Image (tube, each protein chain N blue to C red):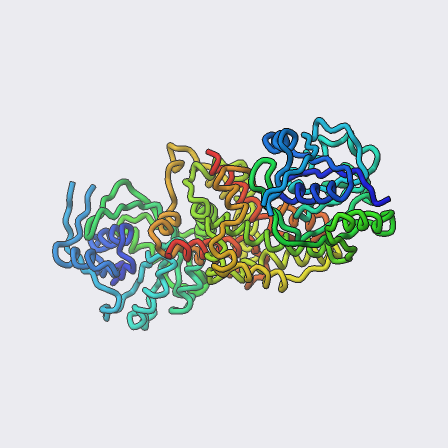
Length: 309
Length: 309
């Protein structure tokens, strides 16, 4: 009775690991992904998991080819690519499946709401890890857990059943009321380190060595706090600030250029509209001024244009 | 009776040209400057003016060596270096000379007020041109004019006499009530082009080619407008915007990197505290929010620190 037909929407490292565990536990799983080499490798040779190499027979498809329907969609697609993924799955969605989003981003609920009724939406965080070694190949270490929060708890049926299914697969899921808070916490970190490192062409340690890192950090985070306050989402600029500063040492991320800096260096459009830009979007709706975050968003967009030439 | 003993404080291209014309017209002139090679060249071989080379015997000194006193100090020192210049001339100032500042900057009055009574202060603009070819050598073309505005008109004696002296020297000076407005206009241009070009490592034409140049420009200038409004200084974001956009073509400044970008590239501290930073300083005093300009100021300071490593 814990059985589910499950789509993994975005079958990168995390989706692929969740999908293997779910299928091996007895569920019917489809991995859905845009990466042709990955989809083909899974379908032609199976998914390889390295812990020692284990090979699993799995089903993978491009979104536009999916005609099946499911009990559960687990979304790992990045906020910036989420809308297009959901558009391409429009026919899959008519049976009103549970949509569990485990992606980073404050914009995910609003995005998913354009495609499915909001009482079908569950948000999650996870500390499972996974690396994407190559097409159809993940490398996995350790254990983890999942924390889940229904977006409309009063109208979401059978969160228990959902949790059972995940726990039957050994995923260590639990209900919690602080998940969207945890999502916003990660967004606050990312909207400081990604954005400033990109603007400055510097790594995380160089940022932390700035004589004005605290002012730059507070300018972003006090706006995040005011927005979160108006949205009635728990948030602590101080806690995020602690987490930011914990990245600074070389032993941690001091010599790391964050993902947005990498996007910029490779002339790829950044996720700025889903980070600082999204705080600014929400602040406008909530009558909370977000001039810093609005400006930072513009600066990154200008930088993109200049880099593309 | 139009005779004056005049100090030129900051004897670069403009100061040197004004000083020559003033001396040749009959006044006693001291050129005051920090550049040792310039001071020595003037004192040892005279000032050369090229129009055809003409050589003039002039007096030049370092500020710390000046013991004379004057009827008029004409200040050409950049806002950022002004305070130190005025400090070094502290003994020169005890006879309460006229202080005419022809330097760019919204911060000049406040700066000079720390060193002299404010009713002694006159602000000016000029369209005289001059180039500084080398130590003790200027190259000069064309004619010009000077517009002057006493800071406290009701308490400044003999603006007429001042104008006579300058006109006797063929400088084409006039009284006007829109000079501080013209100074703020130039500051609005500079606080957009210098600052954004530096942040983006781009030239003026690249800035003008940005798809969001107008938004970036308005973000700075609407704050300048609000501050100017509170300060009761005439200002038009629209007019400044026109002047900004007039720089964009290659025929004009499209391939030019502005002075702040050059400072940054040479690891020299920029004048940001006297541009965007000064609008923010004044806005704070006037209860006008200036979050964009405050942030931009911080970004430039971070950039400086990173460049200095």
